[PDB]
Length: 182
Image 1 (cartoon, one colour):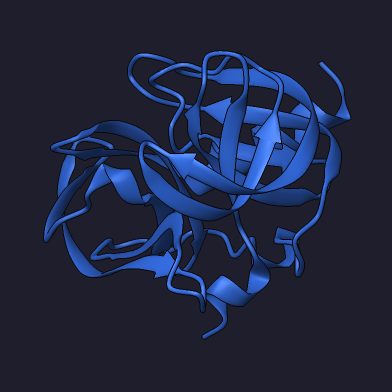
Image 2 (tube, one colour):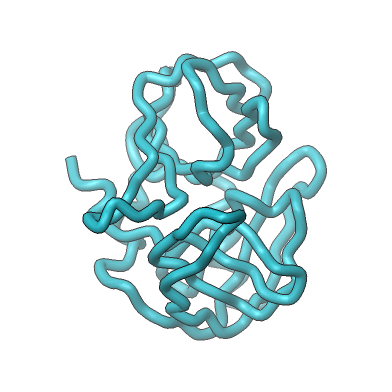
């Protein structure tokens, strides 16, 4: 509908796949080469389904900060025959608050879904499903099951992936440029 939705659509149309684990279907953001991200609660194993195709997992790393606190991001390298467009130059370098964000989801259940979530707070600490978690972004939208892995963007920046909600607020794990240096 406007330039925020334009940037979000450009990311969804080239840099997302549908990932399926034993814990469900997730929006999965591809970042560069065969490297993608998914919420750690997806419990990625040795094999994952990517757009309903059986795919070997070459590496999976559940990130934690240097206090050994959960970040809720798993970085997955996929045994896929095709690379993602490199979007690392759209990742923020530092923790920050944002205005006017969009949460975008693409699954069998929720195809082509875009939500204007508005103002995003650097929330920091969250007890997420009983797990102490750091680098959490918060938005005041009643997100639901089915939105986990959804991409949070502003114009020009890919800032997080949706990892939970409390019925009134939604929560994303930050993406930082430093997670994807090679």
